[PDB]
Amino acid sequence: MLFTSLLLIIVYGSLVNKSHLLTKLINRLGLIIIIYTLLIHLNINTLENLSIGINMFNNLLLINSFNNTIIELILIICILYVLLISFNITGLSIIDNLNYSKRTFIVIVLFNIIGLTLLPLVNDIMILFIIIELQSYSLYLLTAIFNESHNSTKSALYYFIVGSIASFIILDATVSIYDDLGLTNIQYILMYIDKLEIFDLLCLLFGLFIKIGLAPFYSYSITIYSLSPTIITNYISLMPKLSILTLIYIIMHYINIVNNTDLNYVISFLILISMFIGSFGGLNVIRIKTLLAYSSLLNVSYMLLAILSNSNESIIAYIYYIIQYSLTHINIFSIILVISIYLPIMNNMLNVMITKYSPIEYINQLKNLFINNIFIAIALCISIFSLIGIPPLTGFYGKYLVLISGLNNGYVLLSIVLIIASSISTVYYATILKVLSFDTLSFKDIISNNLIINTSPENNNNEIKPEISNVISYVISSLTLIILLIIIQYENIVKGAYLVLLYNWV
Amino acid sequence: STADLYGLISFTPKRDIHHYVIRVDEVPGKHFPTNTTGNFGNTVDFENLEPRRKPINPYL
Amino acid sequence: SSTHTNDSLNSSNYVDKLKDTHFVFENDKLPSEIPDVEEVGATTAPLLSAAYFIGAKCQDYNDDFMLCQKEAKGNGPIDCLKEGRRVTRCASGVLKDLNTHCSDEFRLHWQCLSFSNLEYKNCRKAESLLNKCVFEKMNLVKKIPGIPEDRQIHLKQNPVLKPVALHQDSEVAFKKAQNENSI
Amino acid sequence: HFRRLMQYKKGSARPGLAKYLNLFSLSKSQLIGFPVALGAFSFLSHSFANLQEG
Amino acid sequence: MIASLAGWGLFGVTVRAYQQGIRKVPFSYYPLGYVYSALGWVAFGYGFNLWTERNDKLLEKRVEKLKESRNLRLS
Amino acid sequence: MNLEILDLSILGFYSLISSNSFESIAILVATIMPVITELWYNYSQLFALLYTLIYVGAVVILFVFILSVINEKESGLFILILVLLLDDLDDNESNDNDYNNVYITDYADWFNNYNESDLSVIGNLLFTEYALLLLIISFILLMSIIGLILIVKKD
Amino acid sequence: METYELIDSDPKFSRVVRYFRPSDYLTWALGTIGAPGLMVLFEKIEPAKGNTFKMPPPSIMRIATTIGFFGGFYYAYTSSTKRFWGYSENAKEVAKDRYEVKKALSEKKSPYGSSLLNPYQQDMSARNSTNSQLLLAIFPWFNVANHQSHGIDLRKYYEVRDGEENWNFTLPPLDQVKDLDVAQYKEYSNYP
Amino acid sequence: AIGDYPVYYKQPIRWLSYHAHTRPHVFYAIAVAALGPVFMMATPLRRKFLYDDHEPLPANGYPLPNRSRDKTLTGYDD
Amino acid sequence: APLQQVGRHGGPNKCFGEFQRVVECMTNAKHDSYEPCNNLKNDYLECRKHKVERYKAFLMQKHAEELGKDPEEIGAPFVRKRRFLTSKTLGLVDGDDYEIGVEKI
Ligand SMILES: CCCCCCCCCCCCCCCCCC(=O)OC[C@H](COP(=O)(O)OCCN)OC(=O)CCCCCCCCCCCCCCCCC
Ligand SMILES: CCCCCCCCCCCCCCCCCC(=O)OC[C@H](COP(=O)(O)OCCN)OC(=O)CCCCCCCCCCCCCCCCC
Ligand SMILES: CCCCCCCCCCCC(=O)OC[C@H](COP(=O)(O)OCC[N+](C)(C)C)OC(=O)CCCCCCCCCCC
Ligand SMILES: CCCCCCCCCCCC(=O)OC[C@H](COP(=O)(O)OCC[N+](C)(C)C)OC(=O)CCCCCCCCCCC
């Protein structure tokens, strides 16, 4: 349904006249295609039947209940992202018309969802390399979709080079595996899981570690995320980790058969180093996207401890964490795409150049959001409080579940560092909350009419004029209450994760 | 009861190079694109093939 | 197919230099416990000429030699040494017969094969004479399994693909039989 | 160090290349101090392991 | 079971009520909005309870096998 | 006199000293040619010709095509030979000594009366066994056609 | 675990369409008219430009109907497939399937149909299209070949169940059924 | 409509004529290409009216008789 | 299951038989563990690289060195240039030692 509709959108888009209304309407055709895909997927795919694991397409693709969880999650998060490009994020024509200037935006996104959803299912080194390129090529194109922008093109060039080296490392590990065994199917390799150099699978992981931005490779991800348009950074900083971390978990599932300790020490060396950089790095930053880039690295460090431990509680910790972290990430970026309407306008010093690609770029552009919109400020406060790990939000249960998996497997050193690194990172999450509210009472009664939102035309002066569009507001509210009120249905959700199996059985 | 149920689910059986799940349901090489009978090294017979190890569905 | 291998002669001496190929002999003959057989001495062209008469005469032994390979279950070379000598003796029997019954008809045909790139399509005039001679003096016939008798290729009166150049000894011998035999 | 010296010779006027090469450069003391410390670290770590019987 | 969908619907009313504040509009604006947001989450709430009841049936059967395995371990 | 060593030493000498982009594109052509020639002899003649048809004929002349577009603007003999000599000493890619000093053969057999080229088998499997790999590739090619036009086309 | 009888592990494409229930056609119809409606519903939710409802141009509604025409069929195709695999209610199809196969064996024809594909091509085709409906939400792939790896035992079509003996079908031994693996390798053991 | 561009779903016949006059480089490339798959569909017609498909080649190795080894096989012995 | 180790002619190659015997043992249902198949796994790796057999050749080379056995009398005769596979070397009755024709077949 995804592939067939993609061809129809490719042909149709190249026929009709270049205009914003038609570009925005085609973006609403893709929102249907992704919705239709989820209905067909959930219809045939069930947890109860995919438990054993089912080979598809001459064993090239293997699907089980652990992979199947993430495909539905990926489809869901791709619906919430397409809602941004398909509806108004602000309603001001100047800021919004950027999302509709490109007709191939939705096509490239639909290309990536095919790439993302097939990566966890791969079961052959021949198709592992092909699928990882299909996902990797789609990201470079999306990073350069705004080809007029100098920073966007400079980022895609940086992205392509780093990913090309990353893909070469992945390709070289598979070749080395084929050299030793002569087999391509992953199941056939499992028969020789004790007879092959287990470090050649680690060389495979080193390639997948680059693509998720893990230190010492973290440098490029921070640069890329702080240069792309905020609508682009909202996608490329979350989606690759959804499908690669699922793949990394499976590869580590096979690896722990021989339980090689040297493999675990090197990965612990990278997890430990990344927590240090992910925490101390964000202390001295001014750009919000650079801040969320360091925040992303720290959460990936937590999620690797659940992957590295790889027990029965590690499935629960990973499955829960990857879901709550995606909703938190969408909620935060959606707010940053909206609160740009409250920016002031000059009528000077420090010569800060703002562009239509990142209207909100600095942390102090969040100033006085407690005054301009109190309800959305709390939503950003609740979201940041989840990242801090304050209970009983979603973020606490992610760290609590990760700690169970980590300590149950003897990772005492990493468990303590993650709890040190969490507190160090609380400093720079607290700065976002300091900027949001702390200067409320001095600014309470101010004469503000130079905001960007004050350039909106007055329609009637009799009817009520809401400040924020309908769809984006409903998404922000829904994900803010889900983050806040997870305590109500937490027991059902966690018991719904006990059933996700990866060859546990009995 | 909750402490009992969690103790059952959280437990992870030990896996070594002796017991682990391999998802191959059949022996390849019954038919080849050409020259199916090579040096006759295919000692495996498919007429009297022993039953394979079928997977366990813990929800059935 | 001219792919390089590690089992026979390759394309050029530059392949040998890269691989550092040594062409190794083994003087040791077979042990006396295995009774000796007289190996077939025919070259490529005579064998391709008499291939269908070896198939007609040694059909039972060839099938039995192969069935020993199928049921040896990987130990084929060692457990079919006795059944592999019947085939060698049977095939030597046919080539010895053609040399003592149809020496000129046989030689004419495989000289044609050595003249026309070892292709059966180019030597039908010589081949038809050899088949007719073999039938009367040894009762062997050429049959291609899997098709009706009326639709065998070598009996095709007007073939679509014909030799570009004629074999003089074939055309001369053919028209002589058009007088000796087609009375 | 010698390998990074060859990269210095190839490109010197370029600002970005010397920007990154300077970060990795080790002072003449560090090129001597670092190997001694690790050699001292490995000797003292192993030696104290035998004294403690573990 | 209606009370379970009652709670889910009341969560639907809260989201629409929380949407008004973000948009900065009076909480009585467009009263049909609260019905649509309520019914949307009752549809979600209806399915969510189906999913959890399905989990109970699956988890009871899996635990039947896990108890047997523990007894073999505890021998 | 395995002269394939001398071709790469010259190649390894010019890779250390190349300055402009003309020489950088020359290192590419000077590397494929030893790759093609060492594949023509020894291992695989089919993939020597596929490399020439696909790399030289398709992706190499694209480099020089864009170099004319991009721009054309703008060490010591002791260190180079010292580095090249040091690079020259240790050339054993693997440390299985017996695997590198002991020769092997294969035994041929006559069981394969349907002899056809490798490209016959590769097509036999790519268009039947792994038809998903073939179909994804045409999908990756399709995305590039869209991907090139969105990146480069102005309006 | 709702398990039923496994009619066919790899149901053929023409069979899956011929087994649509009336409700399956309804889903195909609903999917066809749902996609154009979803475009209208979004405009009612929020106009694309301006602040007031404006019907989307007819060209978008035609491409929307096509996209929902395949999506509706794909949902219909997968739902019909679950019955064959046994994941869903298949009692109605089991009798319908048994009637066709018992009739087919009776005429000495193969239940699976004659095939242009050789033995390797038949088995290779089965590998590609078996369990391929699980990713039918991503890209399409259908079993359009008359192969023989359907995951059933043809012995189970000999025994008579309730309400079947009245059909009075005569079933020969499988060794005499045309185009079956148990009836082909009579001359050579590697050629059918 | 003396020269208007035809609408395909209202004037199918005239729509092709517009493209068979103004775009001969597209119309006949599609017309030639479709004649291949069309001819493939008419293969069953040829089977029932012209001639059957040939027998498949013996490209599976040596044809092994489907039986047990002969027990009375003699001759050509040592 | 997917085909692995396909020869250059479409049939099973040298080491396919060993790999197939491994799959039969691993996917068998009468095995409690994977211990019985451990020897079959070695044979498949052995068939491909001959590492153990090359090692055995190394000792027989090294043992003869420590005993003084003459390599030319323990080893097998060989020819390095294909043009000098002459009929004198091949053992033909009246064969010359003149080189053979390996120009064009
Ligand atoms: C052998 C080649 C040289 C060494 C390369 C080491 C590679 C591995 C490093 C992993 C992290 C990659 C860091 C990025 C590359 C850094 C390269 C570098 O050294 O640049 C120098 C930089 C500071 O440069 P600067 O000293 O100001 O200028 C020198 C003037 N000549 O110095 C730095 O910024 C380096 C510090 C970066 C952060 C590293 C800290 C990692 C955390 C380790 C402590 C963990 C503590 C956890 C507690 C429990 C465990 C004890
Ligand atoms: C049939 C022979 C064809 C080759 C004739 C030229 C042979 C001269 C040696 C160059 C080829 C050696 C292979 C390594 C590439 C080295 C390229 C290079 O570094 O520049 C060489 C050439 C002359 O410049 P030079 O003085 O040597 O260097 C400093 C100049 N600032 O700088 C130039 O770019 C001048 C124009 C030379 C263009 C040559 C194009 C690259 C070579 C492709 C053809 C040969 C393919 C490689 C075959 C040998 C591989 C080892
Ligand atoms: C401006 C306002 C500020 C905040 C004010 C507080 C609002 C409180 C609302 C009360 C609602 C109520 O009562 O919910 C009651 C209902 C139904 O409960 P039940 O039938 O017993 O289900 C069982 C509940 N157990 C376990 C308590 C018995 O649960 C809900 O819907 C839960 C809320 C949704 C949380 C998100 C989880 C689902 C999404 C999964 C994706 C990760
Ligand atoms: C079976 C139950 C289905 C319920 C309906 C679902 C579709 C919603 C469309 C209704 C019609 C409409 O959009 O009506 C329009 C209204 C009001 O818009 P407004 O903000 O006042 O705009 C101004 C309106 N003027 C122009 C009159 C001034 O929009 C809504 O209230 C949207 C409610 C949010 C969607 C709820 C979905 C919840 C998803 C939960 C699953 C995860």
Image (spheres, helix red, strand yellow):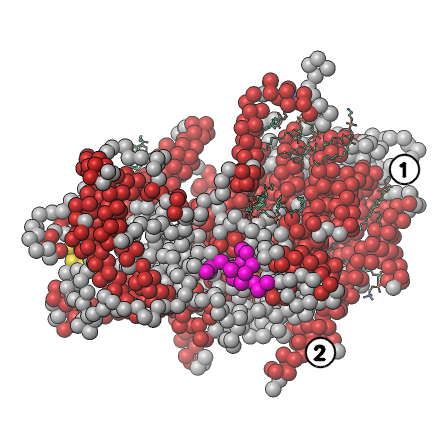
Q: Which residues are magenta?
A: G172-186
The amino acid on which the numbered mark 1 sits, given as a three-letter code, is Ile
- The residue indicated by pointer 1 is A464
Q: At x 86% / y 62%, what residue is drawn?
A: E4
Q: Would you say G95 lies left or right of C149 here?
A: right
User: Residue at the top extreme?
Assistant: H2
Using the image, tell me which numbered label, if any, was put on residue I35.
none
Instruction: Chain letter for mark 1, please.
Output: A
Tell me if residue G178 comes above or below residue B15 in the rendering.
above
Q: Does the numbered disc 1 mark a residue whose Cβ is under 8 Å from ligand 4?
A: yes
Q: Amino acid at mark 2?
A: Asp
Q: Nearer the viewer, mark 1 or mark 2?
A: 2
Task: Give x and y (percent) for residue A444.
Answer: 84, 45
Q: Residue G103: x percent and y percent?
A: 65, 57
Along the viewing direction, whichever of A46 and C169 lies nearer the viewer: C169
Give me the residue at 64% from left, 83% from top: E71
Within-10-Å neighbours for mark 2: few <14, some 14–19, many 20+: few
Q: Quadrant of residue G191?
A: bottom left
> Are labels 1 and 2 on one chain?
no
Q: Residue at label 2?
A: B4
Q: Position of residue G177 (x, y in %)?
A: 56, 59
I16 over C132 or under it: above or below: below
Chain for disc number 2: B
Along the viewing direction, whichever of A269 and C79 lies nearer the viewer: C79
Where residue A3 appears, x then y in whole percent?
Answer: 62, 43
Q: Secondary structure at mark 2?
A: helix
Query: Would you call the spot at circle 1 few (<14 residues within 10 Å), some (14-19), or many (20 or more)?
Result: few
Q: How many marks?
A: 2
Which quarter of the picture shows residue A454? top right
In magenta stretch: residue D44: no
